[PDB]
Every structure is written in C-alpha cells, then in structure tokens.
Image: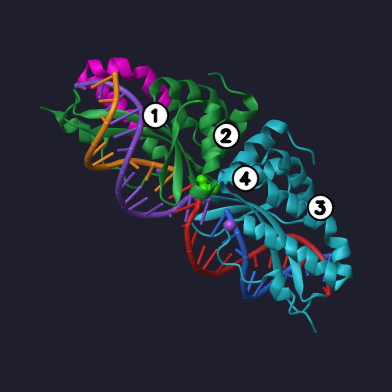
Chain colours: A cyan, B green, C purple, D blue, E red, F orange
Amino acid sequence: TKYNKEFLLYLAGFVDGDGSIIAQIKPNQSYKFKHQLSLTFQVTQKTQRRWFLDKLVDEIGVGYVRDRGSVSDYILSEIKPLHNFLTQLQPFLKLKQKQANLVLKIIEQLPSAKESPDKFLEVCTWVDQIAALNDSKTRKTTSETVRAVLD
Amino acid sequence: TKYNKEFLLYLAGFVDGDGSIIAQIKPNQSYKFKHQLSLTFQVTQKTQRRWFLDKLVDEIGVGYVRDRGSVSDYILSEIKPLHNFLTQLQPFLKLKQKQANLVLKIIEQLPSAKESPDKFLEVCTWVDQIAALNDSKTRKTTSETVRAVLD
DNA sequence: CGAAAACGTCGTAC
DNA sequence: GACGTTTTCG
DNA sequence: CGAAAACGTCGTAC
DNA sequence: GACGTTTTCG
Ligand SMILES: [Ca+2]
Ligand SMILES: [Ca+2]
Ligand SMILES: [Ca+2]
Ligand code: NA
Ligand code: NA
C-alpha cells in the first residue's frame, strides 16, 4: 500500500486542518502492565460530507468510517497499515508532523515495550509528548498515572 | 504571482479543512445600489499558531493576518490578487471548489454588474449560492434583501 | 462612490 | 479535535 | 492477554 | 467557519 504524492500533499493539509494524530494509554487489568497503548489517525467531518470520509477509506484502502451523530470520522488504528500510511504522509505535514514522528517512533518501539516495565513507561512518555503537542483538553490517563504501577 | 504546485496542493487541503471562501452583500447608502459586493478568502487558526498564517502571507505575497483574541485569520480580499490566487488554487479544491468557481465568476462579472440593477441582482444570486454551499448560519443580507431596492 | 481594512460575534464542526 | 470507556475478536 | 472496534462526550478553534 | 457592522482610503 504505497500512495500517490498529489494525494498525500492534499491530505496532509486536510489533516493539519481537521485531522488528529492521537496516542492513548488505556487502563485495563487484562493487560500485562494494566494499560494498553493505543494509536489513532483520524479525520473528522460533518456527516452530510461523509462521502469524503468514505473516499478516504477507498484511497488509503484500510481503516473505516464511524458515525457519531451530526459528525463522522475516518479511523485508522491498525498498527501495521497505520505505520505504512503515516510514514508516507509525514513528509508533508506541517502542523502535526512531530506528533506523526512520535507515533511512528512509538510503533517501532512496541515489541520491546512489552518486555520491561521501564521501557513501557518510557514509551508512555512519548505519548505525553504527543498530547502536549495536541490541543489536549480532557486527558486523564498519563504516563505519570501508569507509574503508580509501583506494585 | 504564480504559485508552486506542491504549495497549492497542500493549501487546498488545509483550506478545505479550516479555510473559508466567502461572498457578502454589504449594506450601505454610499453605494450606487445601496450594497457593496465583497469577497473574502480566509484561513482561520488559533493564535499560538499564528506563525502559520504569517507564513501564508509570505508565500502568497499579498493579504494579511488579523487577530481576534485567541484566534487569527489570514485574509485576502483584493479582487485582482484574489482572482489570481483562486484560479490557481481552484483545481485542487475538493470541498470548496464550487464556491471558489462562483467567486471567480463573480469577480469576472463585477464590471457589468455596476451597469444595470438587474445584472447586479443576478450576481447577488451567485452569492446566495456560495452561502448555500457553505455551512452558513448567521446570514442576514440576501439577494432577496437587495431586491427591496425596488424604488 | 467604490473597495478594502478593521472591528466584532454566532453556532457549530471539529 | 482529542480524548474517554466499554465490548469484540482472535 | 493483546489489539482493534465500538461507543460516548468535553471544550474549543474554527 | 461564516457571516455581521463600522471605519479608512483613494
Ligand atoms: Ca484545525
Ligand atoms: Ca477545523
Ligand atoms: Ca473543516
Ligand atoms: Na497543546
Ligand atoms: Na450549507
């Protein structure tokens, strides 16, 4: 899945505008470290324009559209295709380039982050950075909170 | 003032995201038909990212940035340069392409719209069209409104 | 007058 | 825009 | 368990 | 995002 340059240039600007590059630390006992690292690339749009989101699903060839009322979102969370997509988009972003680099870095690091409790906590630090870059306003689960892992 | 393709492709996506192509019929006795036709190309952005709007002023080479509190806007209203810019940006727009064409068409038509009251009113019809296409919500001055110029 | 700049603000669509 | 919590899936 | 899908909502930045 | 009203400028 290798994309067209004209498309990526256009999409990077659309993303810098209404997209979001999100990293979350999700709490849950089921997981080894009681938290799951989650990554999302998303594009939001008023539902009467949903066709646009649908066309993203067609060109990126992966991901899906969810509806949440008057608004919809194109969503891409699958680690492998997300990494493939972000890598190609990264060179054209201007406003969300750093968070794109951070997500790429987090993905490449997941394997060894399951291994030690200190590698996992470090990676969580990178998600704090992504949220600081974002216009974050209702964040709850922080790397700091994961640190109350101390027994 | 002929722009670089990569730059237009990217800006077209940003504009589809947080930009706005605007046509307004503005009331005022000073004008022959008691209304002034106004066109605006704008890009809005949070003031901590105003550098990004300043960078637009630099590349487009015309227009300016205005501050309105926690938010700012890159503004381009001069008919000649706006026509030039919209013509080159127009082919890459996907969501605001129609309003961009309508604005180009209104601009080309301004000279003859000062001539008859009927041509003027027809042009006002095109601005009703642009507002229909936009996510309009507080429009007051309509082509219908102008029609009560009837003596 | 004609045209742009300046200034101000409602209601979501991010 | 950018999170949150809850449910499915393998 | 691990990872994504599904579902839900706060607070602006358009 | 997409309008509004008021002031300047030529
Ligand atoms: Ca934006
Ligand atoms: Ca936006
Ligand atoms: Ca938008
Ligand atoms: Na921030
Ligand atoms: Na509309």
Q: Is residue B62 above or below residue A133?
A: above
Q: Earlier in the sequence, mark 4 or mark 3?
A: 3
Q: State the mark number for residue A95.
A: 4
**Amino acid at dot 2:** Leu
Q: Chain of mark 4?
A: A
Residue C5 location, quadrant: top left
- Identify the residue shown where x is 73% and y is 76%: A28
- Identify the residue shown where x is 84% and y is 73%: A117
In the image, is residue B116 part of the stretch drawn in magenta?
Answer: yes
Same chain, labels 2 and 1? yes
Q: Chain of mark 3?
A: A
Q: Is mark 4 within 8 Å of ligand 1?
A: yes
Pointer 1 local density, CA inside 10 Å: few below 14, some 14–19, many at least 20:
some
**Amino acid at dot 3:** Lys
Q: Chain of mark 2?
A: B
Q: State the mark number for residue A80.
A: 3
Q: Nearer the viewer, mark 2 or mark 4?
A: 4
SS for dot 3? helix
Pointer 2 local density, CA inside 10 Å: few below 14, some 14–19, many at least 20:
many
The residue range painted magenta reads B103-128
Whether pointer 3 and pointer 2 mark residues with C-beta atoms closer than 8 Å, the reply is no
